Amino acid sequence: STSIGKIWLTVLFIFRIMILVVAAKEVWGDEQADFVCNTLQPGCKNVCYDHYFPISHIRLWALQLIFVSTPALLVAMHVAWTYTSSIFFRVIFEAAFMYVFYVMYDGFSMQRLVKCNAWPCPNTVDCFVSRPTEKTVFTVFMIAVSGICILLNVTELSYL
Amino acid sequence: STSIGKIWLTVLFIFRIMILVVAAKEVWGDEQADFVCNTLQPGCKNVCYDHYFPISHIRLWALQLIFVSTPALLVAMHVAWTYTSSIFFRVIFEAAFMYVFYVMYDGFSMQRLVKCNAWPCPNTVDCFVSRPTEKTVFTVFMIAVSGICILLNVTELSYL
Amino acid sequence: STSIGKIWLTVLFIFRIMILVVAAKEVWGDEQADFVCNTLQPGCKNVCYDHYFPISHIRLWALQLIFVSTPALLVAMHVAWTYTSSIFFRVIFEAAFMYVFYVMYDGFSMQRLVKCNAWPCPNTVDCFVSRPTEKTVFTVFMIAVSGICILLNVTELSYL
Amino acid sequence: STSIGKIWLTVLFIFRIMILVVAAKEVWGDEQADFVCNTLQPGCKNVCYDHYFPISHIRLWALQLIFVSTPALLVAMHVAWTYTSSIFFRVIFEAAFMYVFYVMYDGFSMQRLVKCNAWPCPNTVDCFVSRPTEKTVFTVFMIAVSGICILLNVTELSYL
Amino acid sequence: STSIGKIWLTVLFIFRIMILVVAAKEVWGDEQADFVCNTLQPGCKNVCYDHYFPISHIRLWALQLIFVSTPALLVAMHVAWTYTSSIFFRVIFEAAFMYVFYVMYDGFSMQRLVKCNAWPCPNTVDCFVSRPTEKTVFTVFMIAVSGICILLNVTELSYL
Amino acid sequence: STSIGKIWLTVLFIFRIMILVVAAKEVWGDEQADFVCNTLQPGCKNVCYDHYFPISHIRLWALQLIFVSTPALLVAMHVAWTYTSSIFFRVIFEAAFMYVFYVMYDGFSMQRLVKCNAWPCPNTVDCFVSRPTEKTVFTVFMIAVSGICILLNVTELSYL
Amino acid sequence: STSIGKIWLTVLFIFRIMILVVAAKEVWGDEQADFVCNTLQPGCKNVCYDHYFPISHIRLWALQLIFVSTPALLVAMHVAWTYTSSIFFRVIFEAAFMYVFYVMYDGFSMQRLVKCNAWPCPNTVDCFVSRPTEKTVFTVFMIAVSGICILLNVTELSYL
Amino acid sequence: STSIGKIWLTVLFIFRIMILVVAAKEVWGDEQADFVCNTLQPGCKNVCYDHYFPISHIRLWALQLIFVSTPALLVAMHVAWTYTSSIFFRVIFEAAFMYVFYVMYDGFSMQRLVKCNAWPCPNTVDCFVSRPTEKTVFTVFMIAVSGICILLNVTELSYL
Amino acid sequence: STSIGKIWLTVLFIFRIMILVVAAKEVWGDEQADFVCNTLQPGCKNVCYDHYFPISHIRLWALQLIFVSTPALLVAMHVAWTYTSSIFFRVIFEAAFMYVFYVMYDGFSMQRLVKCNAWPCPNTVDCFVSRPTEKTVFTVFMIAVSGICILLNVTELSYL
Amino acid sequence: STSIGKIWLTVLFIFRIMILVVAAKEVWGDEQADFVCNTLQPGCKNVCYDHYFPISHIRLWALQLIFVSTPALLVAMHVAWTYTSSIFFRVIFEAAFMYVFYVMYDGFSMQRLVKCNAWPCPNTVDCFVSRPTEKTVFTVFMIAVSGICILLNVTELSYL
Amino acid sequence: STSIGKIWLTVLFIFRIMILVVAAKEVWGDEQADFVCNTLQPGCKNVCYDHYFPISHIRLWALQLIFVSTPALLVAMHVAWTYTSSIFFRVIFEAAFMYVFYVMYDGFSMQRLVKCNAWPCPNTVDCFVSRPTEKTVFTVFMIAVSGICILLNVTELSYL
Amino acid sequence: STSIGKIWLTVLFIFRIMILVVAAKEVWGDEQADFVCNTLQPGCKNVCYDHYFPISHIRLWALQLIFVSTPALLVAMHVAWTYTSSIFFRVIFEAAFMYVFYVMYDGFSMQRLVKCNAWPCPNTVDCFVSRPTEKTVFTVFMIAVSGICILLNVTELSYL
């Protein structure tokens, strides 16, 4: 009847791990040498990439998995009331990274072209990103599992 | 007499894993720097590659292995009627990825040449893909095991 | 007196694995960026490489190891007459890959130079392959163990 | 009431490890070929990089994890008074690496541009670093866990 | 008094493994892109490298470790006179690879420069090899352990 | 009172391992393509690098760890007076590699610039090395642990 | 009253010469190395340039000046009825080159961009011409003087 | 008293010629390959150069010398009232080219940098012109002689 | 009635000169650096150009003008029967160069593409020539004047 | 006794002409493509060259020859008191260009290296000029003849 | 009867001039940048070109025309026996340059390929010359006129 | 008997002119882009070329022709004792340039290789000059005519 969510959290936990490590260092790994900017100006590349990518998706997520897994290893070793507390933390972190995500990345749709008007860059330049479609797809999966994990976590935290 | 399919599913499960990991990061790994486009136009490469490859085969498959393996880890931990349910999910996911596959990739035959008429690209350009033959071959194996796994799954789900 | 072949099959099984993984991703890994074609024509490289290498040796072999190892994991889990059946499959697969091998690759001697007259390629071009000698050597070892495994398998399948 | 800090130290220990290994060889790994200097002068690159990066962050930290983990493996095997000693060492090392860190790296804010006036380099050149923002972020996390680990360690060493 | 050689063989076995894997894919891994030939002639590189390196040292050795380790896994599983037989094979293989080694590689001293007069190569060209000194050093260690393993193996096979 | 050194040797043994593997293939791995020589002369690079680096630090050390770890696996399996013998070997090897180290590498301070007057190289050329500072630092740590391990080993070998 | 046209013909004759030789080998001289085509395909340049420029303006004109000046040197040396004949030829040649001009060059407005779909050229490529504006301007001057020379020539040939 | 201007016109006529031919094909001759634009975009060069240089100064001037010299060769051959007419034409042409000059070229001060936002050019690019100072100087001389020639021509045409 | 041909020969003589010198060093001058061959093979360019262009058109013609003008300067200075002799030579030379022309150059139509299978050139390569159309046009003019000069020369040599 | 200076002025006039035209377009002609600046920054070349060379020596001189030759063609045609006037102008122009010369060019010694800190140029860059010695030499000759021409002109203008 | 040779010498004198100046700076002018050597070795080009071309044909000839024309301007101005003297010099110079020619240039047939084994050049390299055929042709013409001029000069010097 | 030298001076005067202008701008014209230095160091080229070529031969000579021709135009216009004076100047200038020549250029033999150790240049570099042989040859001719002109000039100045 209740606490099926424990299962679903384990399922989605392992799921998220596998979604990352498989596509982890085989999608975004090449996202420094594949940022073709249409200029001879040295440095404009690194500037624009730092501009539109303060953090790469995979790092944010990996952190999110840690901060959301930390209450598990927290509640495991407590002694040799706390349940609901660790679970509430498990809500708010998740929600936080989702927020930060949408703020840094207007929506869940990578734009093929990105303009750029930083300093080394003389004027508005046109820099191209790698495989925006596919990254968008993986975003949709991980935000989806995020929303699920939230909703379950909220419901079973509402057990009264 | 029946439930030999449990064996065949384990066999083909491990099989599919081995078919991937062996040829996984040793076939498609070089499928970004081996997409020779016949133009000086910057960016046309990444655009055309994103066009004809929203997702690389191996990612789709890896997902398919997860969504089809999830009902196993689901049914394993249930308590400390559901059988047929997890099995039916195990059908529909498999079939789904096969459909998505054929839609994104007209048939199971990579074309050596691909034309391209996106934006950075001035007109219809001629971009060449890497090793289309061999990838086609591996597609045939994995779709084949897919069809098998379906057919078994349907039959033994038809046990009445 | 008999079924020493079980040992020899285990020995050669592990042997073949070790011959691969050692020289696996340390010989053929560089066999895309080391296919020097004497032309400016874009794409002629990928075309000619796909022409004379529909599959790289290591993939064929890896498959062969799987299809020949599958009857082992097959016979292991059967219940919780079949022996000779799994063994006969173990013959015919092995023989098949040897045939396919010799057909795709006229004999067991990589030619240093390969001509090529596909479409992007204007006329007969001269493309050079990497380390043909050494690959030939490893072919000789793996076909050799193949012939051995066949001969043993046939003899002990002839036990009557 | 007391020695909850043992937990928190294990938690943050494993935490720090995971923060590193995830972003370890996927952030700073490319920090040699992504140091774009605006000069033709050979060697000025390596000179300026050695100048402003005598050590890369990750090495310093990794050492810090070892010197701070060494008193654990020290106190574990002692026989087959020392507690407070190993703990005090565990304070002073941590504090030391924090100091060294702030000295080598004026504050916790990587500057996008760095000037350079070493020998091969004719005059003040303008060299650009990769992803200064993101590295700054990870610095903030690891110094943060550092300050926590200090404060706990000091308090529970003040148990009297 | 006798069969100390069993120890010494285990010691040197593990030794040889460690000498390889450490320097294995960190010395010879770059021995394709570091074969600087002083010509514009396409292909002359791959030709000359195949000429003076039919096999790279590490492959020969790895094989030698397998053929010399095979009699161990052979004698281990025999039943569920042979001792001296497996040991004699263990002699002759070792000696064989030492012979093949000295034949392919005149002595144990890599020459910095190598001339080359194959076909694509118009005339005698001057091709430079990478780090000949260091490879020579590792040759000396592995041939040394080889000679030791031989001598022990011969003596204790002479036990009468 | 005595044989605390057994602990300290285990501590520093594991320490040295961790100092290597962490910074092992993440510092010196790029020390072939980062040896910028100020000449068009082909080959002068490989010549000068072989000149001033007959061996890279990490190899020497790795060997030293093996030759110094070999008396441990030696004394472990002796039967199924020797103590002091294995320990004395454990002294002299350590001291040897320290000597060889200082001879090949005048002191423990990598020079940023290195001149070179070998054969392909027309005259005294100016070749630049990568990150000399940081490598110097790691040298200081490993020689330091070396001196410690010596001093302990000598003292407890002086137990009488 | 009449034969002012003799003057005007001398005036415009010398004029046309000066308009050419001044801008002759200082405008169109660089119209081979300034035909930037957006493709790597060898030869597509020369093909497209030959396509849209069977003849460069200046050659056509120079010929026109010769064929229109030939009746002058013709009528000069006749002996040591013909007047109207040489004059009529002087009309029809002029008119002819004007026609040929407008046919080869749709109007008197060089287009900045020119597409091209010849053979070496894979598909419709985008080739850019040099200084189309300025050449258009000089066309307007020379066609203008052409129309004048015609009109005068016709009128004074209509003297009856 | 009057018609000193005939002298001054001959003086300045020959002057202008000499100012051109000396600096003619030794200043602006290199003004196609010295228009460094900060972009990889093919064609943007020719576009921007055609934009800000519909005509190069020297052509405009050369024309002006012809149209202003034409009334001289006109008045010379008139027969074998007209004076003031040829002189008035000699005014209005001169004034015209001065006007056209100032319109095409905002003032007599070449700007070192010129932005550009034409079609091939993705956005506002920064293109650099060659030796803007020196060309400005020669403009000042030729406009100066122009103003003089005007003023004299007007005065002596005002002879009544 | 007769010897109008003297005029026509002077006319066409001066004509041919003017057709050359105008288009002389402004068409074929760039016919060495505009022979784009689709190969990296050094030297294949010069080989193929020497193959299909033993002589450039303009040289052949220039010679023809000299050998055909030599009988004029011959007959001019004879003293201080011969007429028909110098005229007959004037026929046969002209005819000769026309023959040689058609032999070296199959017809009067330059082919855009030329294949080439000389020695440095590995196989049949595809080399592109510059402006084949326009050169063909000038050939048609000069062969045309050649045929005229012949026909006149033959007729008036047939005066009897 | 007097007006030998007329001779000396003709002598030095023709002299100066010959000194220029010989070394004119054979020294400074290559002074745009031989201004090697040690930076990748586009445009910094043209900027720095315009900075330190507002005018090339030869232009200044050529002007000086014209303004100093203009009083000759002035005094020649005066009619069909003025002597001293044209001669005084002949002094002041000469002196003027000498002044302007020394101002633009600190002394008569071209510096091999020139630093530069204009806008595109990030900081003080090091740009190298071509053949500074030789240009200095020719400066010394032309300033020398200048001083002579002055001194004579002043003396014979002081005839009273 | 005699001294027709005066004519023939004038004819061939002017002839030789015209053969040169036409093909003079339009054949050998590009014979420095069209000497494609198949090596990366800097300098080997200039070395090999200096080796096989101590002097270019056209220089030798031009000298020969001067030394053979000098006795004409010699005999012209003698006063305001010598005839035969100037004529004999006119023989021996001509013959001399023919000898020097054949010595420097084995025969009158340029070889397409030339090997080269000078110092910078590591070993026998293969350098390709430009248009060897055509230069050979012009050699044949000029040596031919040389032999004629000799034979006439000898005969009419044999007038007795 | 005497003043044949007037002839010989005219002969050699015109000779020297022709030797220059023929080989003038067709030998040394390419002596800036053909100074191949074996270094990446920017600027070292221009430095070394300025070092070993403060002046190119042809300039020195051209000056020498002017200073030695100036006494001719001097003595021509003297009026509308001086003879020996102009002739003595004609000696000393000639001798001077010969001296300066031998000083700047150790002897009359251009060395193929030239070392260089100026400032930008890090150490002794190896720079290669173009066609040293041929330039040496022309030096021998012009110094030869120089010595002749001297000797004649001295003798006939010794007429008493």
Image (tube, coloured by chain):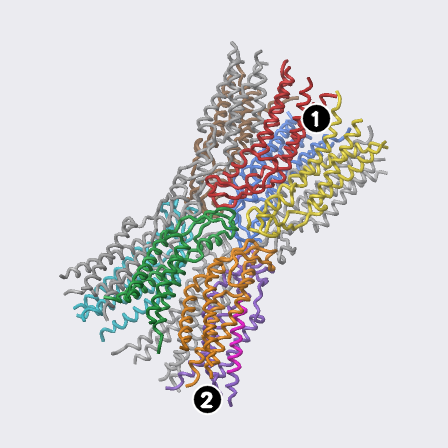
Chain colours: A red, B yellow, E blue, F brown, G orange, H green, I purple, L cyan
Looking at the image, residue I17 lies above or below residue E47: below
Q: Marks 2 and 1: same chain?
A: no
Chain letter belonging to callout 1: A
- Residue A37 - label: none
- Residue I81 - label: 2
Q: Label 1 sits on what residue type?
A: Trp
**Residue H59: % across, % down:** 41, 61
At x 51%, y 90%, the residue is I160
Chain letter belonging to callout 2: I
The secondary element bearing badge 1 is classed as helix
**Residue E79: % across, % down:** 77, 30
Residue F49 visible to the viewer: no
Question: Which range is magenta?
Answer: I134-152
How dense is the environment of label 1, judged by Cα within 10 Å: few (below 14), some, or many (20 and up)? some
Looking at the image, residue L91 lies above or below residue A135: below
Q: Is residue I136 magenta?
A: yes
Quarter the N terminus of chain H occupies: bottom left
**Residue I13: % across, % down:** 46, 77
Q: Label 2 sits on what residue type?
A: Trp
Q: Quadrant of residue I117?
A: bottom right
Residue B5 visible to the viewer: yes
How many numbered marks are there? Answer: 2
Looking at the image, residue L132 lies above or below residue B75: below
- Residue A8 - label: 1
Q: Nearer the viewer, mark 2 or mark 1?
A: 1
Q: Give the CA separation, mark 2 to mark 1.
A: 119 Å
Between L134 and A33, the one nearer to me in the picture: A33
**Residue G160: % across, % down:** 47, 81
Q: Quadrant of residue E20?
A: top right
Looking at the image, residue B71 lies above or below residue B142: above
